[PDB]
Image (cartoon, rainbow over all chains, first blue to last red; front, side):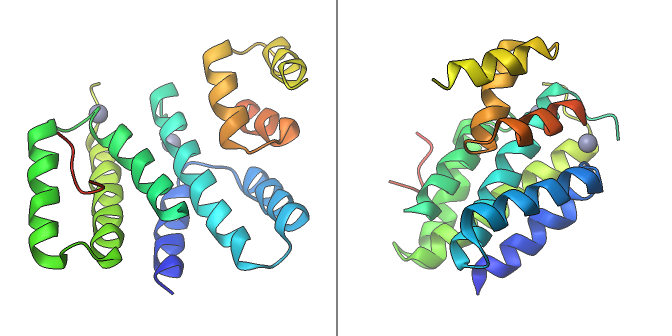
Amino acid sequence: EWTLELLEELKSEAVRHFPRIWLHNLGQHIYETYGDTWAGVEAIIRILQQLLFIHFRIGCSH
Amino acid sequence: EWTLELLEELKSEAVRHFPRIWLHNLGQHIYETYGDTWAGVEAIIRILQQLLFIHFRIGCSH
Amino acid sequence: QEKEAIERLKALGFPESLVIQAYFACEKNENLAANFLLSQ
Amino acid sequence: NPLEFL
Ligand SMILES: [Zn+2]
Ligand SMILES: [Zn+2]
């Protein structure tokens, strides 16, 4: 449950920085690796977090 | 488990942008409000994320 | 075996340190890391 | 020690 509010907070930030084409490819990775199981939601959270930090050190042009 | 890995990533990033004693004092305040329960970990994760996001939106000079 | 993936990723024209970070943040996924790097 | 930063 708490995982869902966290996931919603990551996504709001993520869509400001990542193109829709990349988020679609992320969803495709999560589906093939995890299906629609809850482990997939936790992976998405972890991936978006690390990628956002990697994105900011590179330089956010937004 | 996964929650602790998530928090360790946040703590590593956060310490690059905010003074360590001040983050540490935030942690003591959360400890006073939640004890050793997982709700304390879950609150600080949300707080550290939101602090990082507003920091990057303001402008990270680091 | 996975050093091959990061070398292909570097051959896209990207610094090694960034490539390693993205490749592991994208779990095992070379193509997802590539699409991430090319989106920057 | 998860809430500590030292
Ligand atoms: Zn950005
Ligand atoms: Zn900063």
